[PDB]
Image: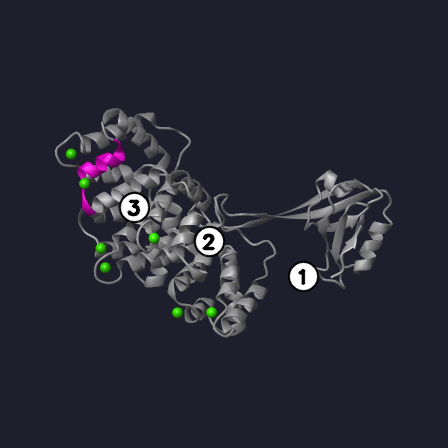
Amino acid sequence: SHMDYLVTEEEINLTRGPSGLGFNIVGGTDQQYVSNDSGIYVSRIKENGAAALDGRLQEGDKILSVNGQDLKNLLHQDAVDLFRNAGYAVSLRVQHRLQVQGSAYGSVKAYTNFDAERDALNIETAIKTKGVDEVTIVNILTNRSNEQRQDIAFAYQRRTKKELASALKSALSGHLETVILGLLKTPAQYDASELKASMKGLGTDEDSLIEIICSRTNQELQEINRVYKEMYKTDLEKDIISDTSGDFRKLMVALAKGRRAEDGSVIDYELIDQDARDLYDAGVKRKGTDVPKWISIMTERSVPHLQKVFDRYKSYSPYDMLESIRKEVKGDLENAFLNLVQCIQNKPLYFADRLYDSMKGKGTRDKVLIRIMVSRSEVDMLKIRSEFKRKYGKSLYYYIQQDTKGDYQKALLYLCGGDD
Amino acid sequence: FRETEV
Ligand SMILES: [Ca+2]
Ligand SMILES: [Ca+2]
Ligand SMILES: [Ca+2]
Ligand SMILES: [Ca+2]
Ligand SMILES: [Ca+2]
Ligand SMILES: [Ca+2]
Ligand SMILES: [Ca+2]
């Protein structure tokens, strides 16, 4: 889930009019646009101008040369003079810097004009303001990508000799602290800490353990397994074994290994039918249930394969997969299978339903609401929002607004990313 | 911060 910059260089030829080339420039050795580069940059493109109609030049481009003359290490005025004296036919060599987001369906995007040192200074200022300036802290952190937050944390520690997460742990409280500390962890660190929390102490928070283990992919689970061992000095599988038993343990342990078959380009029609018939013969068709058979099929096959298996299953069975689970099993095991099949069939709708359940009644299941808003904000929140609005008739934004208040509400609404 | 029209 990582951002990228695509730096490319392009030659652009324009015809000067009475209005000129139609853009403004900034920079120079005497007017350094940032701390380092003395380069010349396009700061604005005038509408209905030469550069605009041509469409190639972008705001933010660096001008490398004008008619073959380089704009490297020039005073601002010397660069202006190259433009003023370039004639009516002007050849530009420019450098484009294009920001690429990690996911197309995330709600939180990388910030364009990002300066980790400035953000760290501003957050320290907000922490040290009398009474704590939570608004500024929320405004910054919910409007930076997770990778940018890691860079802020690094600059903060260097400046203050304190870890940013610890400083905010001390400065904040309540649900807002929970949101902010969650946003500061990497995705694997966050999931690992949420898994540990679901198991630490007497009993188990099966709801949270199931949500994470059933919804994460092989790539996410492999990194969680690695980070969990670094953070807690034990294997995630050993903690699952410690906290669970019976068939529920078998299913959780199997899923947590992250060894599901990857999506392939070959559709295995013969296996689709055999899997569907096996699911029927293991469950609705017989007395009792062959749970190991269900576990093997539903944990080992790829997600696109299982989507087709569940459709073929309806050719054999009078009930669909979800209804069959309800009839065959119970307890933690039923809850796990139901969550898993929902994640296979439509994962954004799965999270939309969990979000609705966390708010629909008296109060709020804040732990679930926060974890989904934090963990899915850079993955598929736009699809979650679309499923939510389609099913429930009002936006996710609307439900968050009614159920939460204060700076905590503000933070969740930023992670939502907008109204629908 | 000088911004110059060209
Ligand atoms: Ca305050
Ligand atoms: Ca605190
Ligand atoms: Ca426990
Ligand atoms: Ca429990
Ligand atoms: Ca049965
Ligand atoms: Ca049941
Ligand atoms: Ca409520």
Position in image of residue A385 (x %, y %): 43, 44
Q: Tag 3, which secondary structure?
A: helix
Image-based side of A371 in relation to A320, left or right: right
Circle 3 residues within 10 Å: few <14, some 14–19, many ≥20: many
Earlier sequence position, callout 2 versus callout 3: 3
Would you place residue A145 above or below residue A340 in this image?
below
Q: Are marks 2 and 1 in contact (CB under 8 Å)?
A: no
| Residues under numbered marks 1 and 3 in contact, where contact means CB atoms less than 8 Å apart | no
Task: Rate crowding at label 1 as few (under 14), some (14 to 19) or many (20 or more) other CA atoms within 10 Å.
Answer: few
Distance from the alpha carbon under mark 2 to that under mark 1: 32 Å
- Give above or below for A170 relative to A81: below
Give me the disc on residue A161. Answer: none
Residue, x 83% and y 52% (percent of image)? A82
From the image, tell me which residue sits under label 1.
Answer: A34
Q: Secondary structure at mark 1?
A: loop
The answer to whether marks 2 and 1 sit on the same chain is yes
Amino acid type at mark 3: Leu
Q: CA distance from mark 2 to mark 3?
A: 32 Å
Magenta segment, which residues? A320-331
Viewer-nearest of labels 2 and 1? 2
The residue wearing badge 2 is A413
Residue A382, image x, y percentages = 46, 44
Question: Tag 1: residue type?
Answer: Val
